[PDB]
Amino acid sequence: MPSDSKKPTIIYPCLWDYRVIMTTKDTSTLKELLETYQRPFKLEFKNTSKNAKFYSFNVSMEVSNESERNEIFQKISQLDKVVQTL
């Protein structure tokens, strides 16, 4: 109060999970690139071949702030398959 009034207040240095679903019959290219595990990141597979409509996949990676959250969102949605994101 005795210094600032309004701020973004964005500080969360922990593992964030994003529910990303894709609607394409050619995600094989993503499942191979997402499984690379280049950086400290993981994905929680929702279904192997049961969801005959929308491919659901989770994304768990180290986050420090909006900076990453903005890079992690654009990196996961890099391809042109994913349609629904959370």
Image: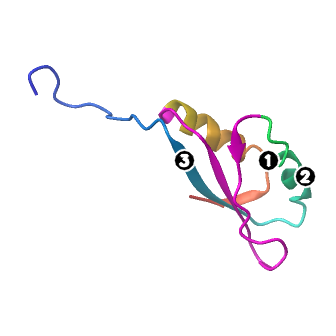
Q: Quadrant of residue 21?
A: bottom right
| Image location of residue 71, percent across then percent down | 62, 35
Precedes in sequence: disc 3 or disc 1: 3
Graded by Cα atoms within 10 Å as few (under 14), some (14 to 19) or many (20 or more), the crowding at tag 3 reads some
| Image location of residue 64, percent across then percent down | 50, 32
Residue depicted at x 85% and y 75%: 49
Mark 3 to mark 1 CA distance (whole Å) = 21 Å
Which numbered marker is on residue 79?
Answer: 1
Q: Quadrant of residue 3?
A: top left
Kindly report the secondary structure that dominates the magenta region of the rendered protein.
loop
Q: Quadrant of residue 74?
A: top right
In the displayed structure, does residue 43 sit left or right of residue 34? left
> Which residue corresponds to mark 3?
16
- Count of numbered circles on the image: 3
Residue depicted at x 21% and y 31%: 6
Element on which disc 2 rests: helix
Q: Nearer the viewer, residue 68 or 53?
A: 68
Element on which disc 3 rests: strand
> Which residue corresponds to mark 2?
29
Q: Nearer the viewer, mark 1 or mark 2?
A: 2
Graded by Cα atoms within 10 Å as few (under 14), some (14 to 19) or many (20 or more), the crowding at tag 1 reads few
Q: Nearer the viewer, residue 1 or 82?
A: 1
Q: Three-letter amino acid code at disc 3?
A: Trp
Mark 3 to mark 2 CA distance (whole Å) = 24 Å
